[PDB]
Amino acid sequence: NKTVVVTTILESPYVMMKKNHEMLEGNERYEGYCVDLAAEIAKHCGFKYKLTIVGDGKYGARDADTKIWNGMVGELVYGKADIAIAPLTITLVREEVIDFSKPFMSLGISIMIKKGTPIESAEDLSKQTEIAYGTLDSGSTKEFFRRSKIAVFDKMWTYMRSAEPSVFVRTTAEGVARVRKSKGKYAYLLESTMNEYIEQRKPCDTMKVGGNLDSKGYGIATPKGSSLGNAVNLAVLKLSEQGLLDKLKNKWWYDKGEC
Ligand SMILES: NS(=O)(=O)c1cc2c(cc1Cl)N[C@H]([C@H]1C[C@H]3C=C[C@@H]1C3)NS2(=O)=O
Ligand SMILES: N[C@@H](CCC(=O)O)C(=O)O
Ligand SMILES: [Zn+2]
């Protein structure tokens, strides 16, 4: 019996620092959907755990050339963490190196715009040039475009990869701030979950437009062949069927809505 090392990321409303975290210790310093989920997964699987924020603040991508994985995926692949409980997207390239539980939350790539922006779809973005658009560095959303075969998406990637100054951002907050401060000249491509969350946060000046570009979900990840895999997957199913996952999404997304 050993304390499970949990890697996660500071991303609202999944994991956030508590107001007086400086006066708290260990897992008590954090709050959010994934903090709540972590406690439940651990309780049902019967293990003690320690939440740790991923060092490089990234989700996970493999550097072409160096072939080294960064972010939470990296912490799992190189043995720094035993499990990842965060808004980590299930993708083929990742499932080839780590294991994923069935999804605990659904999402799709979506468009965030400053209210009033002349955009209603991805096709709209790909057909104009006045409004710039980008995605998060090191994420599944960037990969989606980099490897998309679909016309509208291949065209969009071609623009984004060559846009100057860079249309990519280091963090979701950076993307959101760019939308809010660009007077409608910047649209941000991000997962519906984050988009929906920000839409219910003051100043209530952003909006999700159009339908989602794809359909996927977040899963709890473990190193390939881990002993925790089975139990965690069963826990996710149990918690999903008992309605806890829905309860947690409402608690962190809409129950505390500010708009
Ligand atoms: N509506 S939501 O995003 O909070 C949400 C999304 C999903 C849930 C449960 C909730 Cl509450 N459960 C499923 C899980 C239950 C089983 C059927 C599909 C997987 C395994 N995942 S999902 O379809 O990605
Ligand atoms: N959830 C994504 C990060 C957010 C994004 O790429 O938009 C991932 O696991 O890479
Ligand atoms: Zn429970």
Image: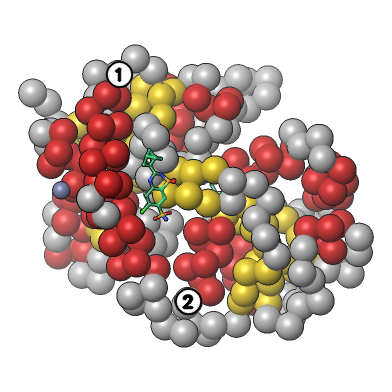
The kind of residue tagged 1 is: Ser
Residue 29, disc:
none
Residue at the location (77% across, 63% down)? Answer: 121
Q: Position of residue 250 (x, y in %)?
A: 34, 67
Q: Which residue is mark 2?
A: 200
Q: Is residue 226 left or right of residue 188?
A: left
Q: Position of residue 177 (x, y in %)?
A: 60, 71
| Residue in front for this viewpoint, 2 or 219 | 219
Residue at the location (18% across, 47% down)? Answer: 39
Q: Which residue is mark 1?
A: 226
| Residue in front for this viewpoint, 149 or 19 | 149
The kind of residue tagged 2 is: Gln
Q: CA distance from mark 1 to mark 2?
A: 38 Å
**Is residue 78 positioned above or below 84 on the image?**
above
Give the quarter of the image for residue 258: bottom left
| Residue in front for this viewpoint, 169 or 42 | 42
**Is residue 256 positioned above or below 36 on the image?**
below
Mark 2 crowdedness (10 Å alpha carbons): few <14, some 14-19, many ≥20: some
Q: Position of residue 91 (x, y in %)?
A: 55, 32
Secondary structure state at the residue bearing disc 2 = loop
**Is residue 231 positioned above or below 243 on the image?**
above
Q: Position of residue 171 (x, y in %)?
A: 55, 55
* Extreme residue toward the top, this view: 225
